[PDB]
Length: 91
Image (cartoon, rainbow, N blue to C red; front, side):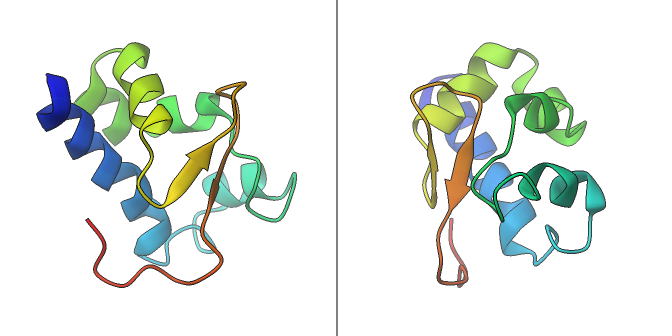
């Protein structure tokens, strides 16, 4: 719980972008395609399977996004955008 599990998930969320896996996984890319990579519903991120398991609750998924490391979640908590520059061994 707390910053351990929140941070686990935080790494895990950015990791899907960091592992150059967004452009590959049309699951991500379908959502990203609403605004390049500035629109990512928490429906997709909750539905990421691995994320749902590590979180066990959408509460933890929502906090993880609220504390995003190299992403920024909107105040609506239904979009997040990542950084222009590629991530380099980020955790």
